[PDB]
Image (cartoon, rainbow, N blue to C red; front, side):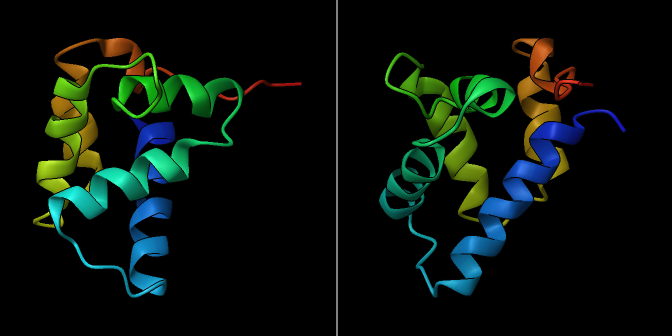
Length: 97
């Protein structure tokens, strides 16, 4: 399960957009993703940074995430795209605790 944290989070995000009847336009996807990333902690907050969706993150990367989302690119494929930048995105694991 390469990219598993990333894949599940993006699928959760997709499902939220669908369930809330949100338009898949670029600006909307961008704001919604930044919003979805707001209350995140730990590994999910690190993922949000790798997605371009935290204050200290790269909007260049945010564009690389939200443009594929506008055509409903499968989450695994978005994650695999980002892995080529910084591979740690696909290596994340939640605390074993």
